[PDB]
Length: 133
Image (cartoon, rainbow, N blue to C red):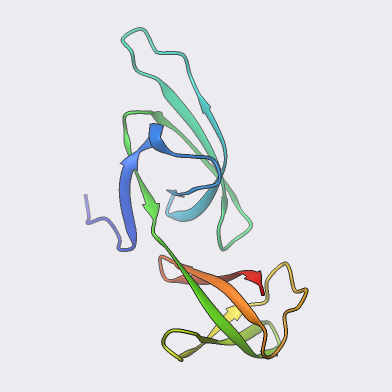
């Protein structure tokens, strides 16, 4: 029931690829591991998919038929220029809209400084810097 929350697309479980993304228990995740079983006895196979939150350091997993459908978050890869770093937020200016927004300070901060360029993503309304320079 209920409509499929925005920002996702539906794909078959058997099409998922390690390193790609998928929604698990409502959390957008990056797939870290995929295990696929031998065909049932009718041809059906189950896949165990393990992911790590894109935006939260949490582990999630599911088991489902490879022919079943699942939601995957659509990733918007963008570029920004750092304007400032204060407290627990990095303020950046998107290089396409010239709008400013706030994002968490990333794991990798080498070269993270006012003026620097960063690649950042938006997925289901959340944001994170993915690479500096």
